[PDB]
Image (cartoon, rainbow over all chains, first blue to last red; front, side, top):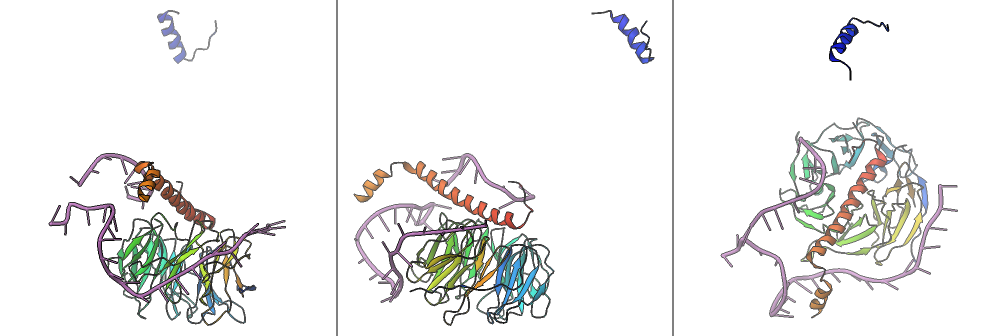
Amino acid sequence: PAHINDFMFEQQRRTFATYGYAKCYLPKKQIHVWSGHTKGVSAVRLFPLSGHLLLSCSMDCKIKLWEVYGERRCLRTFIGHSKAVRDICFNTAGTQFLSAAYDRYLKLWDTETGQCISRFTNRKVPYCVKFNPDEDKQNLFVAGMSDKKIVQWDIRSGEIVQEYDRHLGAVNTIVFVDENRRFVSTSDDKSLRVWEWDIPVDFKYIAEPSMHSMPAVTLSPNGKWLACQSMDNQILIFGAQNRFRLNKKKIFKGHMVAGYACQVDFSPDMSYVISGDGNGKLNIWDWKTTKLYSRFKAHDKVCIGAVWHPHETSKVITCGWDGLIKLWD
Amino acid sequence: LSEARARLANTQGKKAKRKAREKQLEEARRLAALQKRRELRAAGIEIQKK
RNA sequence: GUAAGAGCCUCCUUGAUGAUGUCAUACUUAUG
């Protein structure tokens, strides 16, 4: 160590800047869907009364109006959606429609007029949108959102209808029955719960550790049974509820579930049920025989879902996938 | 007697029973959450992180 | 009757059915 007094002079020179160093039906593909979209199909809709007009919803956030059945070409284009449509809906007559947009914006759409209806919003991103059965007025629509409460919404009155929480899980989809006193509610909690709806109180809840999510939910046209395909690729047919049991049809396996919700299809001859597969193959099932039909691969991409013709006799079944849709005879 | 022998095979207990219900319920909740998450990630590119 | 936890402030597979309601009995409730 050096001297501290010398370090003081060295610091003083440093401040001075001194540098000195000194017998089953076999349907086949009929025709491709009208037009199409690059983005995956968001929802598959169709005209309930006519059946010829199909409304294709895609992830492109543009509602695609399609004319389909016969002389095959689409309908027109529909815009105005803020973000990708989470769900699609339509009125009983078909001239009016409802839209559920992942922007958390529910926008009704007029179709036959060439343009939509109006733009609306909700509290959270709606996970389900469905029209109200029974009374032909239906000022409210049965819907559901990430808030985990099935809520009907009155529209033409300027404000919604009511909100009711059946379960703590986010409602995946809601399909109201014909009795109008109960509406089947499937939620992300995996618990299938019917809900008394018009009354603020629900109905009942069942099967929380079963029926994984809600990949497919459907009911027979006769209303005797409602089957729901589950994300284990396990189709659980539930005998519909009026009873002490009030559930449980049968068990139908053989499908494929990749986790994406697939639109369930059937042939309502009292015969068949057909739905898409998670791998993209076309799932054909014989139903009333308690066993399926056959698995015929159709779409090259992940199958979004499928639809069926009206109920008269065997006719044809439409199909759709991600990025493209194909109808089968 | 049949329920007594089945209970003898059930000797795992309510702890292992709640562990089995938590494993099946956790696998179903992970299959549904990862399910819908995979359905959303395949369409839109906007997602948060875990 | 209650310690703890959770998140939102470019190519495949082995074919067994269903809807009309009531008693002894078993299990789950802080309403006696």
